[PDB]
Image (spheres, rainbow, N blue to C red):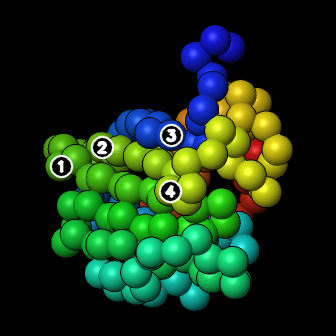
Amino acid sequence: MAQNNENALPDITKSITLEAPIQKVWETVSTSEGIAKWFMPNDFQLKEGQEFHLQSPFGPSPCKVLAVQAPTELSFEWDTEGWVVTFQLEDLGEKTGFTLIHSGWKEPNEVIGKANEKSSVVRGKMDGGWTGIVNERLRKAVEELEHHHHHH
């Protein structure tokens, strides 16, 4: 717990190899449905810069894409706290290596702020959260879509 001080969600790297082709993972992390993860489907549009970020949205602001790279890299900013996530696609044979990158951008606070008031716990929760979420949720969205699966 000594490492956790001044977090607000810093750089978190995760990598998980999906049993799907690179094109299927790409649509899974570049379509409205896949990005929503079926957890509250938003009508997210893949734009190489949907909105630009300068100030911290005090007024209700949605998720905005920073830059979208052609079936290789994806970067978007979700202003709920300011979670900027970047996905990367590694070309493998028979499978695709998905690389998750999490970086929080807003005012560098020690805690995220409003979503949950704690830093160390939120960090630990994000570790376990992201690992489980990106693992099976991407894997399911690339192999199928949804039916009946309990996710945390």
For disc 1, the neighbor class at 10 Å (few under 14, some 14 to 19, many from 20) is some
Q: Residue at x 40, y 86 (%)?
A: 50
Q: Quadrant of the C terminus?
A: top right
Q: Which residue is mark 1?
A: 91
Question: Above or below — where is 111 with respect to 149?
Answer: above
Q: Residue at x 63, y 23 (%)?
A: 4
Q: Real-space Cα distance between discs 1 and 3?
A: 26 Å
For disc 2, the neighbor class at 10 Å (few under 14, some 14 to 19, many from 20) is many
**Horizontal and vertical percent for residue 43?**
57, 88
Q: Is residue 130 visible?
A: no
Secondary element at image label 2: strand
The type of residue carrying mark 1 is Asp
Whether residues under marks 1 and 3 lie with C-beta atoms below 8 angstroms apart, the answer is: no
Quadrant of residue 63 in the image? Answer: bottom right
Q: Which residue is mark 3?
A: 10
Q: Is residue 119 left or right of residue 34?
A: right
Whichever of labels 3 and 4 marks the residue nearer the N terminus, that label is: 3
**Horizontal and vertical percent for residue 134?**
53, 47
Which numbered dot is residue 105?
4
